Amino acid sequence: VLYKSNHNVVYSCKYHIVWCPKYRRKVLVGAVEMRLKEIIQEVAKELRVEIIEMQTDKDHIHILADIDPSFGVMKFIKTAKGRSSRILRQEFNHLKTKLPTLWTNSCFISTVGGAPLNVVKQYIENQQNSNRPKQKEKWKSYVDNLQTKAL
Amino acid sequence: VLYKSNHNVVYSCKYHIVWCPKYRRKVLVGAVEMRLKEIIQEVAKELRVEIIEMQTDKDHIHILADIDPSFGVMKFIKTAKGRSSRILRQEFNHLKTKLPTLWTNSCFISTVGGAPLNVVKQYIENQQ
DNA sequence: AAGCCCCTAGCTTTTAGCTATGGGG
DNA sequence: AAAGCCCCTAGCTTTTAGCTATGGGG
Ligand SMILES: [Mn+2]
Ligand SMILES: [Mn+2]
Image (cartoon, rainbow over all chains, first blue to last red; front, side, top):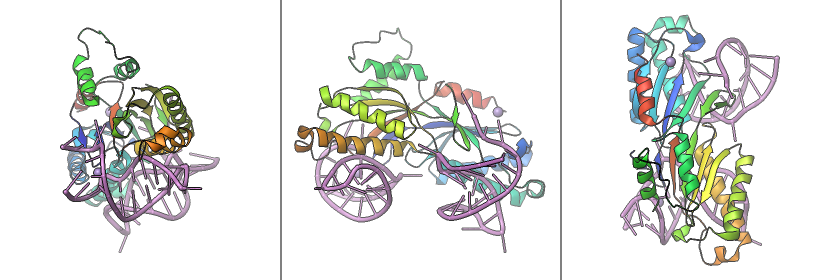
């Protein structure tokens, strides 16, 4: 796991973001799909967001991004959907005439880290004495990174 | 993990947040430690933030919290650090006299989810 | 725990189109 | 060191304070 920092925060903020076109119309196909990803990449590039992975289904776009926690994941999302909708609808007439808006007013957001929730929770508990979790091997690299970043 | 939602978003945003007192003074102990944790819960309640786990070292406070993406993790943090600084320094003389500020301008924030990163990166790759 | 419909101001994409711990049905 | 120390604006809470901002300088 690699950490970045703005002027005041050290962070690692990865989000699995998903959103679908309006009425889940299966429009994210062909040139629309390829164009959409290109627009998202340029939006991320200028908004200093790192697209770790991004794939499209026919009525879904999955994005795994690292976003500055102070910038705001929603600021990235609003920009990506807003611009892509404005552009795509200009380029592909069918999205303009057969749909009131390209996207919906919602999305799905889930945080992603280097280890599953339970181990981080475990590590937090241990702090009160910091003896040794003894685990085995499992998740030792992650926990090692942490204790180092905190001393 | 059980997803929540506001009016327009289904989410699960858990962060591991860590911050320290000014100059890393091992001051988070006894009455102070207890009062700080109290203030944090008080603030989280007020700000609809779920504190999944919170423990203090002596120059660190760890918090695992689920925060609304639209609300903002920083909004939770500034309130938590700011109010706790105000109150603690009001309730503990040694904290106001020996330090210019209780906290620092920085903090550590690490996102956490049900699965590790590579697992989620693979799952996404399989969407083709 | 959204996804449909409708609405508003804010802000971008501005003769658009998506947010807001938005609000209502 | 920079996140952490120093210093500053500016926005908002905690406002006879004290922490933010994809902030910015040593
Ligand atoms: Mn600074
Ligand atoms: Mn899918």
